[PDB]
Length: 243
Length: 234
Image (cartoon, rainbow over all chains, first blue to last red; front, side):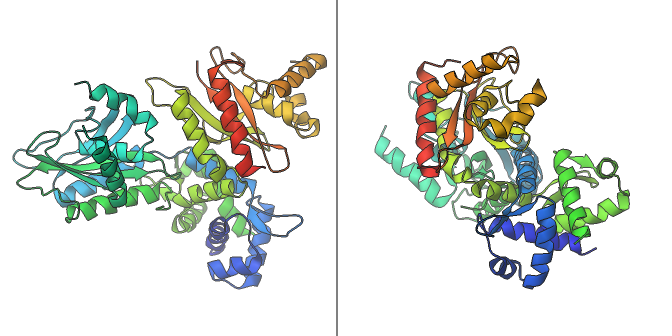
């Protein structure tokens, strides 16, 4: 019955309580009487899901807590978690949305939800976008280390203003997304936001696209919030705490 | 208090059977009726320790499980201490890097940072590598009290003892071991210890691919592992 909830509701608040916690701080977190917490604590210590330190008496997560968690982290897959919200974001905007991840050649489109209109522009799965010429490529540059972008970026500048470049990447973070007006192809406007994993690493970039007529790619227009709501959702479902 | 633990029991099956499982396969594993399992599954879903996949009777671990994984790692001063430096080192090294703590069953890998690269070589976060068959374990053998690992060493049975002794003196003198092929024909290995506040080995940092005790990669690994000690150890 009810006892399964309270058990892991306690485990969830133990994790939330840093590395070590006392009983009163624990019961105050999950909002239950101290006595019931102490009772279920005992079970969680038996099951290995919690431990009590020998010299300080503080409660912390057990090795069972660690092993389940590492199974979870081994199971993260932005391609799984994103597939439904991508299609939902497409259906509310009726604009083509796509997911890209970072591959040996940069932004690589791996999944696409097209807009159904008489005629529509699209990326296609398997397309590699430019690092500095697309909105997908700029979010990547904004959020990945300098070291894993620089080489392909240097291959790109054989085909200026570094200062302006550095101020723009600081902008894309301050703002959390990026809009482009035809930069990759004039007359097509894109919008891009990043998706993070549990550990905060850039998992993917999610991106809305469409010609200037129907789609206004403004960094603060109702598409932008839908975009962010979608990407913050995909993130939080992968464990990301939002900071 | 009794059925508090069947809740977590189903959690542990969900982990063993991850990424996903049919409810029926999950029930056979725990040896309980499928209806009883199905109901406990909803308790954890409300808690967020489990979700239900696109097949509306197929389950997988929930977002809270990641939270508990990461807190557990924070709680042993490995997470926020090694999170960055492990990914810096992958960046410069051009090869997959990973971190392993000493767990109940041996060296258990707690974070894997893989290179961006046509073909890499990975190990699963949360998997266990052998004490004597892996550079990650051999290092643990070199720097851990003989007491703590004598069980698995005896369990795996370099047999002759004096051969053991030579290799583990050498690994301490050098400060790392690099394997070639003891996991599998074609490993690169190269592992180095990480020391906690009191000087014990709290983790091992292992880069992998298809392997030198002496060249360029060894210094940046030793540089990153010798550094990482002070914000965890001192």
